Image: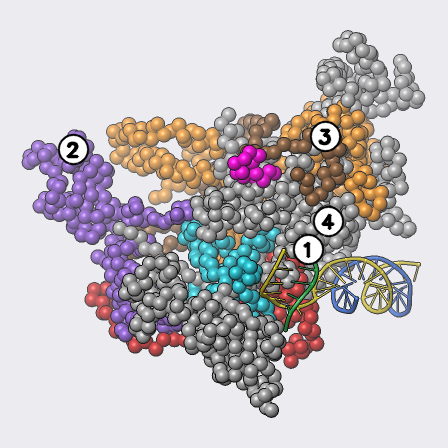
Chain colours: A cyan, B brown, C red, F orange, G purple, H green, I blue, J yellow
RNA sequence: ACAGAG
DNA sequence: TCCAGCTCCACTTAA
DNA sequence: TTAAGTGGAGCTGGATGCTCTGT
């Protein structure tokens, strides 16, 4: 939330982001701007590249290609605002190796 | 409640008879008043019907119907020679065909 | 050298950055955020998630800095270890039956 | 409209007169050029006949039937050819006279209408894997039964 | 007995491929069809309707009422789509400028692309080269469309192909019948005299017939784009696996899940736009039956295009006065774009927890790498210490002290469990005995924690540095005045921010890279910034 | 052409199978390609690509050409894939003009794609043995005698020839021989002295080598074009008048282009000798018909001359525009009803018209006409002109003149046809695949009767066939056959609609 | 009668196990995921046979465990068609005779492939066989189930995967025959 | 939406 | 409040 | 004489700092 009245918390702006890049601090930038804000998991079907739910893909009517991806929630939100605009972000996922 | 647009620009100058609210979605196959024309029959239009079915049964047997190759057979056995699918092979005329296509 | 490596003097404007940077999500996170996203839909463009800005958007660690290298654990391991010999299915006893 | 439940019976009654008159020339079979002339009706005689049948108390004025017969052209059932009023019992137009004859359609109904697809109202929605598919269509499952 | 299944398929994103859905793929994603205009039932039970918007088959946005599709709460649910059928096609306002481009390249009569066999052979081999980049595609689209616009007759059918251009807000016109002072061309001369029935009854046709042209519209351009040959689609620079020309005209529309547009803003502007689209779809459908004039149907269609376009982008320039919104509303574009939009406001930078703010005041008895943190902040800002052989006996004493004494702990969490026991209740001397290796104790901030420290305007990297915390009673943050020059701080009621990194890897990157002792010199000219200041120089 | 490519995928799978429809569809969809990337874009192994390309070139479904640096590029001929659907109509129409020997010639040419003249006369003789009994062989003479009659009538034509390497460019072998068509010898047959007999399947060096022959599909379309014109005249005027048209078109055959607005004129003086002797008509009455046809506003015939007595030409393009319109009006009538078909013919004759004139002229009231008008927009049968008063184009200040455009509505209606046939095939294949259980079961019981039919076959096996539980099941197999026979027959009959619409679209294009 | 299957996997070794040789810890963590489970197209995995190759042990960010791609071979009970096996009857049932093969219990002898003399049990669970000279139709497949010899004519895999969103049928099936001479109870031949 | 603070 | 692309229209060369 | 390639002028759409602290 936004501030002191609402026990809101503090903002890591676009300028503080530019500072941390210049230190090469890749994991701290991941901790601050993902883990301690909006960490989430989505089911992604590797066949159609769309998001699914509960390990089920309604588009394919199958259960075998679905996988879990660690994603910021604001990006999941973006990936559902864009589909309603009919801009489809079809993902492709490799293994983490 | 009023909307963003003015309803008077669309129509409805009297102030009533707005269209109703659809409760259940319409069915997937709605009923139609008109029906297809029945087919043409005859001694000639039925001979084309029988020739059409004889071209499927022939061209699947002709050597142009290249079937997909089998694979990952598990073990070898003596019932391989008794169950070998035998079929003769057609050969093209390699003058017309390009040099890049010899097997 | 960044302004001149493509042979033309490119500005640090949105127009120069669109000639330098390939990534849709980098371009869409600066200016003209609608137009770049509809163009990527039309062109069917695929976006490399390699760039810094889209790594922070997608929540993956950036390549620059501490992300440029990988760490291996120095476990006490023997790669290509001694194999168990087969006894039965070895080639010298199983010459093919058919001619 | 004049009356929709009124024109619908006059529409068939006029065509039956032209079909009758065309049938007379086809039964006559004397000389094909003369037979073609005999296949035409007068624009005034068809009006004088329909008003004489006595369907209604209101008079079937000639200025209406002259435009009612156009509906038989747009149904594709009759031709119209204007001829000069060289001779005629009235000559209803200055220098001109109108002839009408019933005609058959150019070709039988096509092949597309015979198939169920030709008439479908949800044709844009039908796809192989979808909710609406040829493999689960009700229009085909009905029409193949009878 | 049981079949093998992989336990936890974690994967890594390799690329995002953008594209567009066909109208019959939308129907395959969406769980329901939406047909009802009313948001809520009229009766006092305050339920939403079964087949309107706010239906809980499309998810939930309140803990009170669960989602219907998967039976799960707000916290567990990803959301699900519905669709609206549109009775007439409409231009998508984001794709509109691309719709015109294709119609400038294709022949309007047979839908083949207007290029010779040689130019088609040339560009198709340009599009073969490996590693074609996004800039090269945009340049190639220009050169392709350039040639198509300089031709006026099709090589394939022969029909004339005049200019295609915009003619007002979401309208397209084709100059098929240009006229000139020269000898009149055959095909235009036939068209100009075909109006014989109209001229007999309408006098005003006879001036205006010189301006008669082909008014392209969604019912026509959807029928053209179905007929474009798939061989010619790559030369429009459309990728034929991400979309088709047919998909650019929307005859169906997805409605977002409820968590995209939460129930108390009451309803969001997207939900009220979708009501208006559904209402106008009922208006147009009825007027077709009840025999409205063509002037009314066309006007209603113009409204349906506007309401869809303002649903996507509510800032359109060319809106006529008798159609302009009285109130401003968030379209999808307005919540993406700008400083308070997704990309700047919620994606590139975002509000973070384990953070604090207070007035700063001097303390020269601290070292330059230290910062004084007040006890009131230290009792709140906790760090998750993982229990292991080196700290088990230390964390036990912290668990015993509990939340109210400063070297203490607020939460305890068991090894393979994700709920947290709030340590204010229960008997802490029992919970200390039942510590196992692999438990997490959320201890208070203590002396020697690596803590980030930052003034609000940052012009260089030294504006955020890492300091070793030391806990002290008074409320302000305190640091040695030698570090005032990097932060540009001046102790006149200034405030500074503090961040507590919640991860061992984030401590090390903060300590080694961002420590004050590692940052005595500015990157710019290599000059020292942490040095003596007034009353240390005098 | 997504409807075309979907339909081409099914046809290649039914006649050639899976690993060749992959290559066929890929060529139709992408255009011309070198060989190496056909494999790579598909993931097929290189040997299977060669097998797939060599069968598609045998049946004349792909062309090839040499390009820069000597690479061969193949190119699919999309329309020629769709003409595999009309094959039973070709085999029937040759049985109408010619005997059963001429039927079997065209069957072998269409199924093998190309044959040498020696090979066809052999295989027709072999297959006609089953049609006859009691010692009488088929002999190769009465086969060739029909083939040389087929050749003169242009139903059969020679393929493009290999060039003479010794005369032209002797030396290093080219990547592909760059075939060319010779206009002299397309209809000049080799002379064959060898004769023989067809073998009756007992089961217990070549002079015309390289002279390949194939069916001339364009000659069949000139036949089917005539039948559409002749039958239209048979309805409107008379059977006698239809024969006069059939007489003009049969003479026109050899001396006119298959695509031209007008054929060669003929005088009525030379029509008279060409008409069959049984038509008891005088020369003077023959001139009565020709003027009454030329008076018709449908204008199937015109004058176009005055020398040698009365001169008359038959209009090829203008007959097709009539037939395409009659096809277009007939689908309006069945889909929306006669009162809507009234409005379609009204707007088509009153070329631009407004709502108040439609209700006035058709005697159809409001709220019934307008509902019909607005549907015809949404199915693309009818268009709006929209003449503006102002450069606003605002709906309140413009007159919405309706229009029917025949060419766009013919292209639109043709697109409905290609998807319609694809749906009919998809229904048949679905019901055939989902009954493979019963079809194998009904085969195996009949296999007990077919296998060991006569040798050692005791009578004690004829009752054990109905003893299986398939006897109640049989009701389904009668439902299967009645479904398939209606789906197959509709797949033939929609081709009658395609040929009428496509021939109109084919003639309006100049392809300059 | 078994087969080897060559498989690859990425094994997570957690950091408390760093005191142990990696080839020992990998094999234990692979047996825990494969033993007594059916892998769909290949059969029932008994145990790991050996590790044939072992790639680099990466440490990925945000974790301390080591992930290493392992190449290994596993002994899997996949029997080829028309093979002879010996095993004990667990049960008699109206649908046929159910045979056990140690670990494996889903072996079906269908009545369409049983011995022809007796084919429909007279309201009895136990299956019967009638020979004119010896045993008047009382000969039976005893509930104690003395070993039968059977020939595996058919096998089938059923994909036992979730249908629909989440919040027991036999996945590997084997079909025998006993009609040939020399097949049956061991005491009969 | 306005005022503040640095 | 300031600034790049896109399109319309006169203005010479060239056949 | 005019087909066409390129100059110059007007229209259009984009952008304009970082946070807390209150009503
Ligand atoms: S719904 Fe069925 S019958 Fe109708 S067009 Fe589609 S496939 Fe044909
Ligand atoms: Zn999927
Ligand atoms: Zn849900
Ligand atoms: Zn064209």
Q: Which residues are magenta?
A: E37-52
Mark 4 against mark 2, which lies toward the viewer? 4
Sequence-first disc among 3 and 1: 1
Q: Earlier in the sequence, mark 1 or mark 4?
A: 1
Q: Is residue E412 visible?
A: yes
Q: Residue at x 70, y 27 (%)?
A: F368
Regarding mark 2 in the picture, which secondary structure is present there? loop
Residue labelled with disc 3: E291
Q: Position of residue F279 (x, y in %)?
A: 71, 24
Query: In the rendered image, which quarter is residue H4 located in?
Result: bottom right
Q: Which residue is mark 4?
A: E170
Q: Main secondary structure of the magenta part?
A: loop
**Quick one: which residue is furthest to the left in this view?**
G134
Instruction: For the residues labelled 1 and 4, say whether their Cβ atoms are less than 8 Å apart.
Output: no
How many neighbours does mark 4 have within 10 angstroms: few (below 14), some (14-19), or many (20 or more)? many
- Foreground mark, 1 or 4? 4
Mark 4 vs mark 3, CA separation in Å: 26 Å
User: For residue B19: magenta?
Assistant: no
Labelled pair 3, 1 in contact (Cβ < 8 Å): no
Q: Chain of mark 2?
A: G
Residue at 37% across / 38% down in the picture? F437
Q: Position of residue E520 (x, y in %)?
A: 54, 85
What is the CA distance from the residue labelled 1 to the residue labelled 2? 78 Å
Mark 4 vs mark 3: same chain?
Answer: yes
The image quadrant that residue F283 belongs to is: top right
In the image, taking residue C88 as reference, residue F24 lies left or right, namely right
Residue E268 position within the rendered picture, expressed as x and y whole percent measured from the top left: 60, 48
């Amino acid at each position: 939330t936004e501030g002191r009245s609402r026990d809101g918390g503090l903002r890591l702006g676009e300028m503080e982001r530019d500072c941390l890049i210049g230190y090469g601090a890749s994991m701290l930038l991941l901790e601050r701007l993902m883990i301690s804000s909006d960490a989430f998991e989505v089911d992604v079907c590797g066949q159609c590249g769309l998001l699914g739910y509960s390990g089920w893909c309604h588009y394919c009517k199958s259960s075998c290609h679905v996988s879990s991806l660690r994603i910021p929630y604001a990006c999941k939100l973006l990936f559902q605002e864009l589909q309603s605009m009919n801009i489809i972000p079809r993902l492709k996922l490799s293994k983490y190796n | 409640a009023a909307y963003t647009f003015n309803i008077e620009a669309v129509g409805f100058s009297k102030g009533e008879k707005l269209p109703d609210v659809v409760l259940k979605p319409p069915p997937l196959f709605p009923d139609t008043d008109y029906k297809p024309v029945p087919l043409k029959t005859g001694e000639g239009e039925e001979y084309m019907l029988a020739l059409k079915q004889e071209l499927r049964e022939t061209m699947k047997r002709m050597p142009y119907f290249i079937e997909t190759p089998e694979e990952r057979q598990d073990i070898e056995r003596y019932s391989k020679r008794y169950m070998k699918v035998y079929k003769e092979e057609w050969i093209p005329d390699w003058r017309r065909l390009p040099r890049e296509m010899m097997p | 050298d960044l302004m001149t490596y493509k042979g033309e003097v490119l500005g640090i404007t949105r127009f120069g950055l669109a000639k330098m940077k390939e990534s849709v999500l980098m371009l869409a996170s600066f200016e003209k955020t609608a137009d770049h996203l509809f163009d990527a839909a039309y062109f069917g463009q695929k976006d490399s998630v390699c760039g810094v800005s889209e790594c922070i958007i997608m929540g993956i660690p950036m390549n620059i800095g501490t992300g440029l290298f990988k760490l291996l654990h120095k476990a006490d391991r023997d790669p290509n270890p001694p194999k168990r010999p087969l006894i039965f299915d070895t080639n010298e006893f199983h010459i093919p039956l058919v001619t | 409209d004049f009356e929709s439940e009124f024109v619908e019976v006059l529409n068939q009654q006029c065509f039956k007169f032209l079909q009758s008159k065309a049938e007379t020339a086809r039964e006559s079979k004397q000389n094909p050029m003369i037979q073609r002339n005999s296949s035409f009706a007068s624009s005034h005689e068809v009006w004088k006949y329909i008003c004489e049948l006595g369907i209604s108390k209101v008079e079937l004025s000639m200025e209406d039937i002259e435009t009612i017969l156009n509906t038989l052209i747009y149904d594709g059932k009759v031709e119209m050819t204007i001829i000069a009023a060289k001779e005629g019992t009235v000559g209803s137009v200055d220098g001109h006279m109108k002839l009408y004859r019933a005609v058959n359609p150019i070709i039988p109904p096509t092949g597309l209408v015979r198939a169920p697809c030709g008439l479908c109202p949800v044709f844009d929605d039908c796809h192989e894997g979808g909710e609406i598919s040829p493999s689960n269509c009700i229009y085909m499952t009905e029409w193949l039964e009878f | 007995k049981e079949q093998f299944r992989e336990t936890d398929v974690a994967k890594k994103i390799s690329h995002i491929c953008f594209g567009m859905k066909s109208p019959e793929e939308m129907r395959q994603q969406a769980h329901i069809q939406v047909v009802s205009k009313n948001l809520y039932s009229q009766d006092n039970q305050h339920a939403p309707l079964l087949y309107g918007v706010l239906d809980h088959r499309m998810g939930t946005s309140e803990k009170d009422r669960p989602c219907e599709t998967c039976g799960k709460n707000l916290a567990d649910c990803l959301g699900h789509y519905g669709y609206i059928d549109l009775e007439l096609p409409c231009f998508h306002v984001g794709y509109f400028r691309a719709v015109i481009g294709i119609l400038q390249m294709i022949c309007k009569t047979c839908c083949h692309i207007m290029l010779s066999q040689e130019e088609k052979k040339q560009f198709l081999d340009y599009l073969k080269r490996p590693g074609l980049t996004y800039l090269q595609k945009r340049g190639l689209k220009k050169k392709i469309s350039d040639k198509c616009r300089k031709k006026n007759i099709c090589h394939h059918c022969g029909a004339f192909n005049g200019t295609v251009k915009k003619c007002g807000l979401l309208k397209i016109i084709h100059e098929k019948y240009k006229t000139n002072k020269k000898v009149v061309d055959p095909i235009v001369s036939n068209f100009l005299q075909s109006f014989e029935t109209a001229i007999e009854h309408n006098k005003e046709v006879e001036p205006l017939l010189g301006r008669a042209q082909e008014n392209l519209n969604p019912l026509v351009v959807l029928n053209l784009f179905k007929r474009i040959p798939a061989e010619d689609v790559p030369l429009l620079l459309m990728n034929p696996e991400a979309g088709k020309p047919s998909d650019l005209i929307l005859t169906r529309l997805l409605v977002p899940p409820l968590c995209i547009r939460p129930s108390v803003v009451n309803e969001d502007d997207l939900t009220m736009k979708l009501t208006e689209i559904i209402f106008l779809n009922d208006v147009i459908k009825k007027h077709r039956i009840s025999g409205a004039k063509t002037q009314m149907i066309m006007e209603d269609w113009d409204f349906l295009q506007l309401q869809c376009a303002l649903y996507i982008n509510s800032e359109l320039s060319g809106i006529p006065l008798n159609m302009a919104p009285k109130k401003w509303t968030r379209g999808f574009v307005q919540r993406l774009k700008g400083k308070q939009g997704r990309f700047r406001g919620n994606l590139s930078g975002k509000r973070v927890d384990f953070s604090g703010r207070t007035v700063i005041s001097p303390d020269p008895n601290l070292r330059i790498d230290e910062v004084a943190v007040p006890v009131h902040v230290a009792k709140i800002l906790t760090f998750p210490e993982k229990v292991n052989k080196a700290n088990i006996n230390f964390l036990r004493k912290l668990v015993q002290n509990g939340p109210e004494v400063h070297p203490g702990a607020n939460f305890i969490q068991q090894r393979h469990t994700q709920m947290k026991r709030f340590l204010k209740y229960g008997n802490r001397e029992k919970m200390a005995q039942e510590l196992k290796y692999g438990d997490i104790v959320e201890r208070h901030l203590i002396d020697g924690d690596v803590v980030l420290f930052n003034r609000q305007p940052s012009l260089h990297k030294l504006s955020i540095m890492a300091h070793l915390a030391r806990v002290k009673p008074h409320r302000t943050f305190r640091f040695n005045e030698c570090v005032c020059t990097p932060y540009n701080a001046d102790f006149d009621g200034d405030e500074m921010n503090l961040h507590l990194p919640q991860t061992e890897e984030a401590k090390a990157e903060a300590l080694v890279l961002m420590g004050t002792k590692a940052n005595l010199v500015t990157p710019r000219n290599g000059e020292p910034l942490i040095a003596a200041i007034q009353d240390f120089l005098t | 052409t997504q409807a075309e490519i979907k339909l081409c995928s099914l046809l290649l799978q039914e006649h050639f199978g899976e690993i060749v429809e992959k290559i066929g569809v890929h060529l139709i969809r992408t255009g011309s390609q070198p060989l190496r990337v056909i494999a790579h874009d598909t993931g097929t192994s290189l040997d299977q690509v060669k097998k797939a390309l060599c069968v598609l070139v045998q049946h004349n479904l792909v062309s090839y050409q040499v390009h820069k640096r000597g690479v061969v590029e193949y190119e699919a001929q999309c329309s020629r894939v769709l003409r595999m659907l009309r094959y039973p109509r070709y085999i029937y129409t040759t049985k109408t003009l010619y005997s059963d020997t001429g039927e079997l010639i065209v069957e072998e040419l269409l199924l093998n794609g190309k044959l040498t003249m020696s090979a066809v006369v052999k295989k027709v003789a072999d297959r006609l043995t089953e049609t006859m009994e009691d010692g009488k062989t088929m002999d190769y003479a009465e086969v060739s005698n029909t083939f040389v009659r087929l050749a003169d009538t242009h139903f059969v034509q020679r393929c493009p020839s290999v060039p003479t390497t010794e005369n032209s460019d002797p030396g290093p072998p080219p990547p592909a021989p760059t075939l060319v068509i010779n206009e002299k010898d397309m209809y000049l047959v080799p002379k064959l002295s060898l004769i023989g007999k067809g073998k009756r399947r007992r089961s217990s060096p070549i002079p015309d080598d390289g002279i390949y022959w194939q069916a001339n599909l364009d000659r069949f379309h000139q036949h089917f074009r005539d039948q559409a014109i002749v039958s239209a005249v048979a309805n409107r005027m008379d059977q006698t008048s239809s024969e006069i048209v059939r007489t003009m078109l049969r003479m026109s055959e050899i001396t006119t282009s298959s695509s031209a607005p007008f054929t060669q004129p003929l005088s009525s003086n030379e029509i008279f000798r060409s008409l069959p002797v049984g038509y008891n008509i005088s020369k003077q009455v023959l001139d009565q018909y020709l003027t009454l046809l030329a008076d018709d506003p449908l204008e199937f015939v015109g004058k176009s001359g005055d020398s040698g007595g009365g001169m008359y030409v038959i209009n090829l393009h203008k007959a097709l525009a009539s037939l395409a319109t009659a096809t277009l009006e007939s689908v309006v009538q069945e889909r929306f009803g006669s009162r809507c078909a009234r409005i379609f013919r009204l707007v088509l004759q009153k070329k631009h018209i407004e709502q108040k004139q439609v209700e006035d002229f058709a005697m159809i009231p409001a709220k019934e006409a307008k509902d019909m008008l607005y549907k015809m927009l949404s199915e693309n049968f009818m268009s709006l002109q929209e003449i503006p008063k102002t450069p606003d184009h605002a709906p309140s200040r413009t007159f919405y003149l309706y229009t029917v455009n025949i060419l766009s509505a013919a292209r639109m209606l043709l697109h409905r046809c290609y998807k319609s046939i694809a749906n009919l095939i998809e229904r048949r294949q679905f019901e055939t695949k989902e009954n493979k259980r019963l079809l194998e079961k009904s085969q195996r019981v009949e296999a007990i009767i077919a296998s060991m039919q006569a040798t050692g076959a005791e009578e004690a096996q004829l009752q054990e066939i109905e003893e299986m539980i398939t006897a109640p099941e049989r009701q389904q197999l009668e439902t299967l056959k009645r479904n398939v026979n209606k789906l197959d027959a509709s797949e033939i009959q929609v081709d009658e609609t395609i040929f009428l619409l496509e021939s109109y679209i084919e003639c309006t294009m100049k392809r300059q | 009668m078994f087969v080897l299957v060559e498989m690859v996997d990425t094994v997570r070794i957690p950091p408390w196990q760093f005191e142990r040789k990696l080839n020992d810890s990998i094999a234990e963590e692979l047996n825990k995921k494969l033993a007594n489970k059916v892998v769909y197209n290949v059969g029932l995995c008994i145990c790991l046979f050996d590790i044939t190759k072992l790639e680099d042990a990466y440490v990925f960010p945000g974790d301390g465990a080591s992930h290493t791609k392992v190449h290994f071979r596993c002994v899997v009970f996949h029997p080829f068609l028309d093979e002879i096996l010996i095993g004990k009857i667990k049960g008699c049932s109206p649908e046929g005779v159910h045979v056990s093969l140690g670990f494996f219990d889903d072996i079906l002898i269908p009545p369409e492939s049983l011995q022809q003399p007796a084919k429909f049990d007279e309201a009895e669970q136990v299956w019967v066989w009638e020979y004119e000279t010896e045993e008047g139709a009382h000969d039976l497949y005893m509930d104690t189930g003395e070993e039968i010899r059977f020939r595996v004519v058919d096998e089938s895999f059923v994909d036992t995967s979730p249908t629909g969103p989440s919040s027991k049928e036999a996945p590997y099936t084997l079909v025998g025959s006993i009609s040939e001479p020399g097949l049956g109870l061991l005491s009969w031949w």
